[PDB]
Length: 179
Length: 178
Length: 179
Ligand SMILES: C[C@H]1O[C@@H](n2cnc3c(N)ncnc32)[C@H](O)[C@@H]1O
Ligand SMILES: C[C@H]1O[C@@H](n2cnc3c(N)ncnc32)[C@H](O)[C@@H]1O
Ligand SMILES: C[C@H]1O[C@@H](n2cnc3c(N)ncnc32)[C@H](O)[C@@H]1O
Image 1 (cartoon, each protein chain N blue to C red):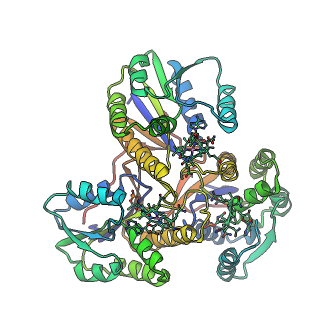
Image 2 (cartoon, rainbow over the protein chains, first blue to last red):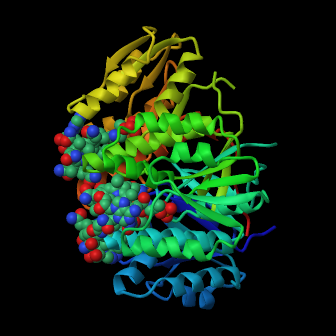
Image 3 (cartoon, each protein chain N blue to C red):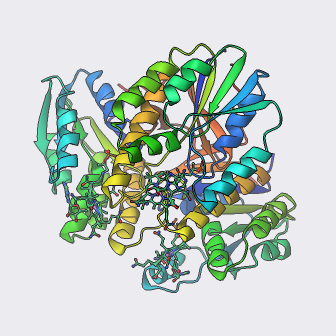
């Protein structure tokens, strides 16, 4: 059972990137970071420059700020393992541009199940707080939850990362109750 | 391993409804949605109309915006499975109306332990964010946490749903340490 | 295997404290609550008065608002189980003072791995909401995230408490996928 797709979900500073990187690097495959993120403020400019300087020379980086599905179709193959650094930031680029988010979330789950070579998606959980007091935050919260539902379904494996520790929730049989 | 009561907890758009609906249809009993809110804005009006179109003729609807406990005691019988749509919206009704929340929370947990028929409670986790900046939201966060704890103790089974996927957390031996 | 150090993580009003207290009281060593919390409002005062009336006189209090690593090295002995009230409030005290958080967190991880006696850290998850409106809250989200990771590494056991129910996530075999 070599898997062809893994979804890693966790909160903010959960350890999910470090965990993703560790699976990618123990694969003995040719590694490509698919990057959805553009540092456009100082806070964000830190994280990219600083934590990139602690990736091996072994990694290759391709940017995909909008056309994530298209990039995966083209760049995926059996010698390569692709890592999508943030589904979260990709969805945010689309939301802020005014795209309707259903078709591309739907395209991404399709692409993930029909992929040439293996891929790891890293995504945030944003759904476990108080309902946001603005239409934008609320609309993102729905797209993020739906998207993580459609990836988790399409992907062979799914792991949840809490406090730097990983827990497989797929593969694995879901509970079924007897009333 | 037979049960009377299930709590399904998850975040917003976690797939907890889908999951409660699947366990409900799996039982073959007669099926009642206990709706705990009508929709008073456009966004809510829509979420409650896709839900309506995705339930076939096996499903009946009884409203209980406030007297959820009483309604569960009248309607719960062995031919029936009741699904409480959102505990979260119920607590929201009580909180805004100015009710003290401890007595009705305790009465729901007591009611859950003693029902004539089976029931699935669907509820949100709301306590994994940054401390909210207003007394109303902090009070909701305290009350939804107590309510999820008292239902979870009362209920036979508890499932946690992430990214459309359920994990049982009750029954199951809890950790112990030397 | 008898353990040195337990991390207890979960959301607001999840049963973290009650769970921590149950394990502490089942251990039959001497019980010290390492309080980190100044009730400087009505809500906060009621929270810690409902806690203190639910504890047999078997419990002794000790305040550590700022110097929590130091306080743990000085009070820990196998004759004693120590329970820190809230890692979260300790972090908050430091953030508000203007301290740089990295050193004091790494110091605390170090100390937890090398204790004279058993300790339980009780800590909040705050990473699963929408990004905060303001830098103060963002800075806190990243620090509480980093702190839970390092304390999970350093502690022998990690539990995750949802709706009053503890799941053990460490020790246990981290899932490994192969592609
Ligand atoms: C959430 C808010 O953050 C800003 N924004 C959007 N994308 C980025 C980015 N990659 N880096 C920094 N700021 C960003 C915009 O101003 C948006 O409204
Ligand atoms: C959080 C805020 O949402 C509004 N409110 C309360 N209940 C509902 C509902 N079912 N649908 C829409 N809006 C609602 C009120 O204005 C409340 O103060
Ligand atoms: C988030 C805000 O909470 C206040 N604050 C800090 N510590 C406490 C406490 N123990 N109790 C109540 N309020 C507190 C400060 O004013 C800070 O700005």
